[PDB]
Image (tube, rainbow over all chains, first blue to last red; front, side):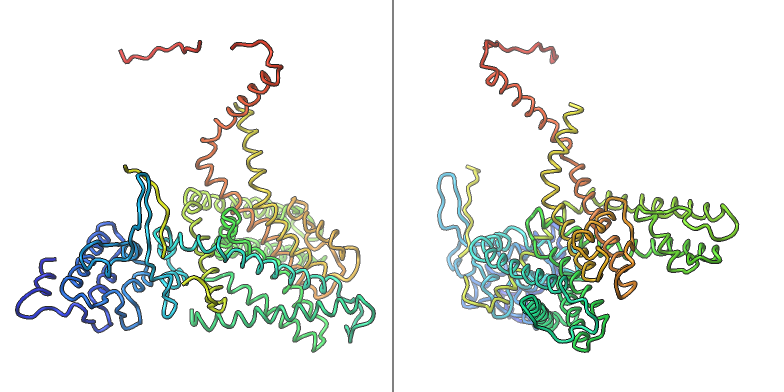
Length: 442
Length: 148
C-alpha cells in the first residue's frame, strides 16, 4: 500500500492511475487477475482495490475507474466474472462507501432502517449492462467448464435478482413455452401413431376427415421441427466454437432427426420411419429438460443428466467389454442353432443383466457343463461384480455432491431466463435493487 | 419405535417419490412406448396399451426384450429397446438411490421424533375423542445427577 500511495502522491512523477498494460488491464484489472479465491487472497485484493478507488476519488474525481475496459472489452467486474474470481466479484458488486465524494464510487446504498430492520440497495451495473455484457450474462453463459463458475451466481445481488424476475414476469412466460411444446409432442406422436399402414405410402393423401386431421398433424410436426433447427443454429453461431450444454445439444439432435425423416419420406423410402421413430423418442425424453426447475423436480433432473454423462463412458464401455468377451466365448462354443451368431448369443447374454436371463438356454454345442460354468461366472461375474462397485462410487459422492449440486439447477433457470429476455427480442423489460432485511444485531 | 420408524419413512418417500419420480418414469416409458407403437404395424403390440405394458415388464424384472416379431426396420427397434432398458430403469435408478443415500446421511436421524408426534396426536384425540371422559386433569420427574 505505502508504495502504491507514494507512486500516486509523490512530487516527482505521480503515477497515471488509469494506465493500461499490454493486455488493456489497469491496476483494478490486474488485481482481479491476481485473485486466487483463497480467503486471505480475497481479503488483501479486496481492500487494495478499495484503496485504489479511495485514491482515485481523492486525487482525480472525474475518472470513472471501474468502467475502463481491458483489450477484450472487459470492465474489472466483467473480467472477475469471466475468470471465476467470485469473492472479488461479490466484493465489487456489494461494496458501498460513504465519504465526501463517496456517492459516485459506491455500488449500493441503504435507504432506510427501522429499530428492527434493514434495507439494502444495489446498483446494479451487471443487470443493466445490455450493450456489452451483464455480470449475469457472462455468468449466464455459464458454459461452466469449471466447477468454480457455478458457485458465483448465488446471493449478494445476482441470485435474488434472478428469483425476483421469475415471480413478476418470467415464470408465466416459461409455462406457456412448456405448454406450447407439449402440444407439439402430442401431434408428432399422433400422426406417427395413426400413420397409414398401406405400402408405398402414402402415396398422396387427404380423403375424408381422418385424412385431413392426420395431414395437418404431419405438416405441423415438421414445422415444429424447423423451429428447433433454426433456434439451434443460432446457438451454434453464438457459442462457436466450443459438454457445456447437453439440453442444447439434444433439442438440436431431435429436430435434425425429424428433418432426416422428412427428407426421406418425400424421397418415399420405406425405412424413413427408422428416422421418425427416433425423432419421436428423442422428443418425449427432452420433455425432461423442460420441467426445470421445480427445485424438487429440478434436482432429480440434474442428477440423471450428470450420471448419464459420467456413467456410460466409465461403465457402458466396461459392461460392453464383459458382455462382449463372454458372448464371443459362447459363440465359439456352439456349432449350430442360431445361437452361434455373435448377435443372437450376445442378445441372449444381455437378458441376464435385464432380469430375464435364461441360464442354459441352448441345448446345441459341445463340452457340456463348461459352458454353464462359463455362464455362472459371467452372470456371477459382470452384473454382480460390476454392480457393487458401481453403487459404491455414487454412495461415496452421496456422501457429497447432491448437496453441492442444487445450486447447479439454479444456473439452469438463470440461463433460461437470461436467454428469453435476450432471446425474447430484448423486448421492453426492467432495465434499483434492495432487499428487505431485518436482523438484530440490535 | 422400531415399527414406527419404518412406518414413517415409507409414507414420507411415497409423498416425495411419486411426483418427482413416478412422473419421470412415466415420461421415459411413455416416450419409448410411443416410439415402439409407431414401429409396429400389426399383432396387438401396436396398441399403445399393450406395447406400453410390454415395456413396463422390463422395469418389473420380467422384461421380454425383443418380444414382437411383427414390424419393420429390423434391429433399430432393438437398439430402441436396449437404450430404453439401458436408459430408464438403470439411468433413472442410480440417481434415485443417491438422493436417499444423501439424506441417509441425515433425516433418518432427525425423523424418529416424527413418530413421537403421531403417538401424541393419537393420544390427544382419544381423550378429546374419548368423550373427554374423566381422566387425569402435578408433574415432576425423578432425577439423580451429580453434579455433587
